[PDB]
Image (cartoon, rainbow over all chains, first blue to last red; front, side, top):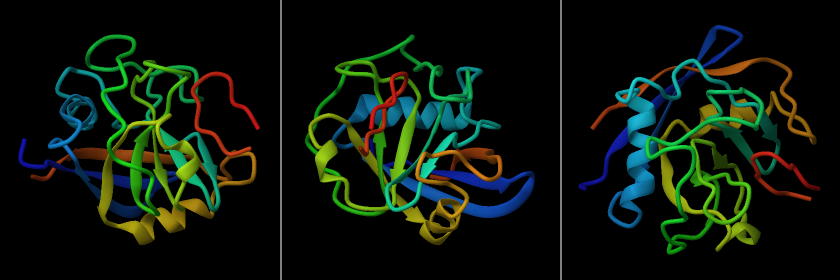
Amino acid sequence: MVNPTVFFDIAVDGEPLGRVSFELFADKVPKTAENFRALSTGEKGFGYKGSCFHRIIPGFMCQGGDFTRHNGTGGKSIYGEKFEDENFILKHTGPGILSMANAGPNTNGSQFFICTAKTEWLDGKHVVFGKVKEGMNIVEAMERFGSRNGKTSKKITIADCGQLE
Amino acid sequence: XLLVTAXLVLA
């Protein structure tokens, strides 16, 4: 589809931080973009609103989307427990890339990461499906609440999310 | 190392 734009309003311990909006490349990975779009609108009656980024590693990425377990073990797609790696056409080209976290081939669920650096070593292992459109400075501010091991000094949540266009 | 997995986090 003509590329959807989704927003996340980030909060830190309840205090608002701001909005990051994403362009989803539904023109190259339609199935993967669509799973992330619908979890952002919560239209299948489940999704990202209220979940947290449970692992933030400065200089690398911010990981979230585990709305089931909040720690890396849960989450699910709108297509069921997991779905296949649609394609590896897009690469991890620099800060702002949005890509799917997984537990090996074809295990995509709901977990994702926002790259705060170019992560070329993940190319061909993780499906890139979007990029930050506005609010990269909100993402760089979220990096500061993480650590080498990804534990966060505060609870970073997606207080509200939806589609813009 | 630097990976993004869901379940067994490696180094």
